[PDB]
Image: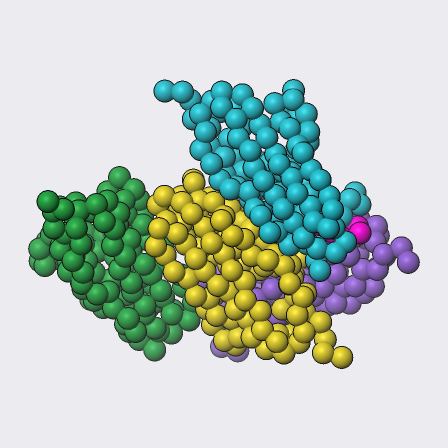
Chain colours: A cyan, B yellow, C green, D purple
Amino acid sequence: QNAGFVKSPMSETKLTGDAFELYCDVVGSPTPEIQWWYAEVNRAESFRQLWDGARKRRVTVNTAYGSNGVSVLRITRLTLEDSGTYECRASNDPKRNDLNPSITWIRAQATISVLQKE
Amino acid sequence: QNAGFVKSPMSETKLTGDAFELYCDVVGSPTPEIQWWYAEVNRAESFRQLWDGARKRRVTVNTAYGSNGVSVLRITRLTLEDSGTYECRASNDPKRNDLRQNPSITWIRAQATISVLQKE
Amino acid sequence: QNAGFVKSPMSETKLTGDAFELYCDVVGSPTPEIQWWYAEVNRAESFRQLWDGARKRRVTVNTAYGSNGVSVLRITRLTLEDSGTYECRASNDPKRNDNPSITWIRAQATISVLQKE
Amino acid sequence: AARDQNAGFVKSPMSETKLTGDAFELYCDVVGSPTPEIQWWYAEVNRAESFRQLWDGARKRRVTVNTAYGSNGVSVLRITRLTLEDSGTYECRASNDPKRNDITWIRAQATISVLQKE
């Protein structure tokens, strides 16, 4: 089985200072890798990988692997510039990390909108 | 600006001659539009919109809109060249259908891989 | 194939607070363009075009162009003032957008909204 | 196309097999009265739904297009640092129809096959 999404991240609107969590759950054989990506504008030139501890540890990534892969992306103390398009990426392609990055992966996107308190 | 995927399409392996169905389920206020897109290689240069009747009518699309958007993409009599990356796209942005824009900019995407194997 | 309605929108009665969805399905070769128009009274002077996002984003238009043109018009949080004649217009005439609107066909539906009293 | 077009191929792109990391160059040379326009198109699978126009700078500048119009039209398509995903059908399209940009184009196709380092 090529990687497939069983749970996808879900768009959400938030207030600055709040926090959000996005979830990802993927199946396949071999077990797929999960990565979280982001772009201000939903276009390939804008997408970059996020990681546990990004943005001075406002960003947290907890990922676990078994038969399936599961992950939560969490961002606290939200700012306006956290708005944009977030993405769970999954692949069990053996060449998936060989240095256009989306070519061997699948993607499932969510929109995050952060509004200013009043 | 608020559409989200409740259920995204699921990757699958099929044999030549069979059929597949992909399913896409989305929430948003107002109700988001749904589209289906495809590419042999998962890069924006190769993605094109599929539609009801495509590929000599082997492709059907059935979509229903209420509070949610729900759609099924079905392709019958599968061939090797039906393999690739398929994609549900959703949006309720009022400018989602303007032409002066990289098609993905006002949409969100949820992808599945379809592999079609030769009966032999 | 000249643009032709395979399914035309159907008149409905609603109560305030509800939503309605009208449906328009047109065949043709090439595939016809679809527009939605509205008027309080069925007179030419009162018809104007509905756009996605109108009426404080209570108006949605989701149109798909395949073999057929298939469109749904949805309006939420219905008020008494949303009552009227709603119309799907279709055309695959090459100069349909370039000679007034004589190149489009119309199919109408009445939406009557009553107070949830 | 027989009524409002008369351009014709004098040099056509040539199929070729290459290794990942290498570069290729395809050539097109077209005659007619008036001078015909040249475009380069590509598809993974030789079918109309997959064909898209390429341009100078495509694929993160790996794709180069150099076209000159004198009496005839001549053009070179170059792709460097080749990947497996550069494989497929490339074609030169040409037309000297007035309405050509509003089919009244003609095409000459080549197959590119990229193999990895064994």
Nearest to the observer: residue A15 or residue A105: A15
**Residue B23 vertical position relative to residue A85 in the rendered view, above or below:** below
Count of number-bearing discs:
0
Q: Residue at x 45, y 29 (%)?
A: A14
Nearest to the observer: residue B77 or residue C68: B77
Q: Residue furthest front?
A: A66
Q: Residue at x 39, y 52 (%)?
A: B68
Q: Position of residue D94 (x, y in %)?
A: 60, 65
In magenta segment, residue B31: no
Q: Going by the image, does A9 lie left or right of C34? A: right
The reply to whether residue D17 is visible in this rendering is yes
Q: Residue at x 32, y 53 (%)?
A: C61
Q: Quarter of the image containing the C terminus of chain C?
A: top left
Q: Going by the image, does B11 lie left or right of B93? A: right
Nearest to the observer: residue A86 or residue D63: A86
The reply to whether residue B101 is visible in this rendering is no
Q: Residue furthest right?
A: D118
Q: Position of residue D44 (x, y in %)?
A: 68, 63
Q: Position of residue B29 (x, y in %)?
A: 36, 43
**Residue B85 vertical position relative to residue A42 in the rendered view, above or below:** below
Q: Going by the image, does B5 lie left or right of D25? A: left
Q: Which residues are magenta?
A: A91-95
Nearest to the observer: residue A52 or residue D18: A52
Q: Main secondary structure of the magenta part?
A: loop
Q: Quarter of the image containing the N terminus of chain C?
A: bottom left
Q: Position of residue B101 (x, y in %)?
A: 48, 45
